[PDB]
Image: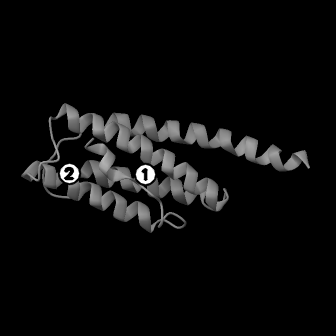
Amino acid sequence: DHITKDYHDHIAEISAKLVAIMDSLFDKLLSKYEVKAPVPSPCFRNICKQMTKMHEAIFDLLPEEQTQMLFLRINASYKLHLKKQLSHLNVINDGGPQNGLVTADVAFYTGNLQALKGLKDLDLNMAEIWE
């Protein structure tokens, strides 16, 4: 019976070093992210293409709930770093031109993420990036 936990205990470990990879990727990219047209920006197109690739790699591999938990944590890291850069660039949620560009770029990001199998109903809480 222990065999049951043997799996879930192990898989939780692969999930952790998968989110670290994205955390590193996000830090690298979003640290040099600059708000400008068009949208999706090259930075965001790169990011979505990467999350699409990882999703394709683990989907058949992990149970749906784990895949869902995994991409919630990836999204959490994404929001963490994005928020950080927005604050750095002094961009705020005031309804201005630059605000709109980021909001549009983010809209593309969630549009993509939500289309990935098993992830359509994720509670993403994207507003957090503005704080």
Q: Residue at x 33, y 57 (%)?
A: 109
Above or below: residue 76 compared with residue 122: above
- Where residue 6 sits: x, y (%)? 82, 44
Give the distance between the C-alpha atoms of the residues marked 1 and 2, in whole angstroms: 19 Å
Q: Secondary structure at mark 2?
A: helix
Instruction: Between residue 59 and residue 67, name the one nearer to us.
Output: 67
Mark 2 or mark 1, which is nearer the start of the sequence? Answer: 1
> Image check: 104 left or right of 112?
left
| Outermost residue, left side | 97
> What residue do we see at 48% from left, 56% from top?
53
Residue at far front of view: 131
Please give the name of the residue rendered at 24% of the width and 55% of the height, measured from the top-left corner. Answer: 105
Q: Which residue is mark 2?
A: 102
Residue furthest top in the image: 88
Foreground pick, 129 / 27: 129
- Inspect the image, locate mark 2, and give the three-letter code of the amino acid beneath it: Val
Residue 126 numbered mark, or none: none
Q: Can residue 40 be seen?
A: no
Q: Quadrant of the C terminus?
A: top left
Q: Which residue is mark 1?
A: 50
Vertical side of 95 occupied by 86: above or below:
above
Work out whether residue 116 or residue 9 is closer to the camera in this orientation and state it: 9
Packing grade of label 1 (10 A; few <14, some 14-19, many >=20) is some
Which of the 4 image quarters holds residue 89? top left
